[PDB]
Length: 34
Image 1 (cartoon, rainbow, N blue to C red):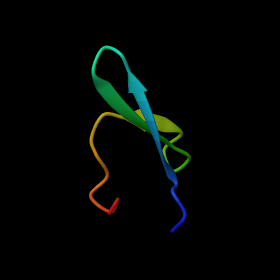
Image 2 (cartoon, rainbow, N blue to C red):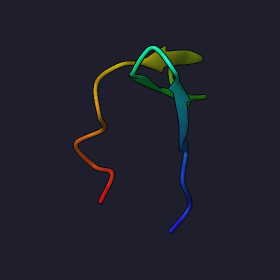
Image 3 (cartoon, rainbow, N blue to C red):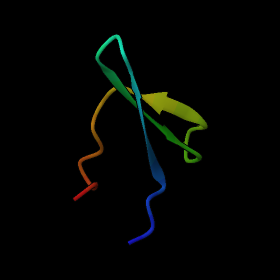
């Protein structure tokens, strides 16, 4: 499927998903991402 949620993981131990829906990197794992 098309991943509109991009996986960015910083060594700090934070996975921030960058999406063009809010133009925002969210630290909440997308509930639709499966």
